[PDB]
Length: 48
Length: 52
Picture 1 (cartoon, rainbow over the protein chains, first blue to last red):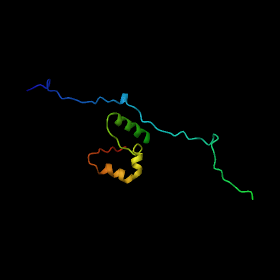
Picture 2 (spheres, chains in turn red, yellow):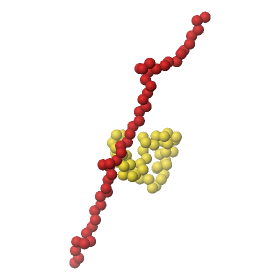
Picture 3 (tube, rainbow over the protein chains, first blue to last red):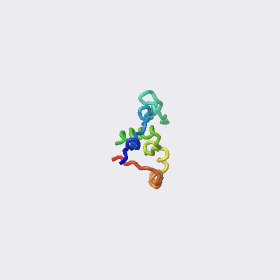
Picture 4 (cartoon, rainbow over the protein chains, first blue to last red):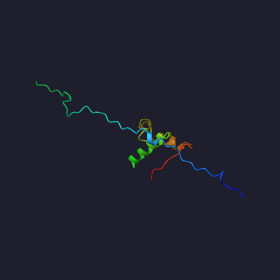
């Protein structure tokens, strides 16, 4: 008989870098609000 | 499960796997959605993850 002492099997486990991983970022455009005095289209009429 | 899938994609990208998902590939996916899907479905080497 032989003993597995020296030849024992190996388990594996990755060295995950999640602890130092950057996050996913969401973008939102800062709308030029119409609540603030934004301009409007100058629909014109004629006084005949 | 959109939020959990975003977290999962963060996990995979951090660990070096190039993950293709619709929310991030929006620009290319917008040109032709079905073409975008077929690109990854046809390729045998691409691993597909099914989020149940």
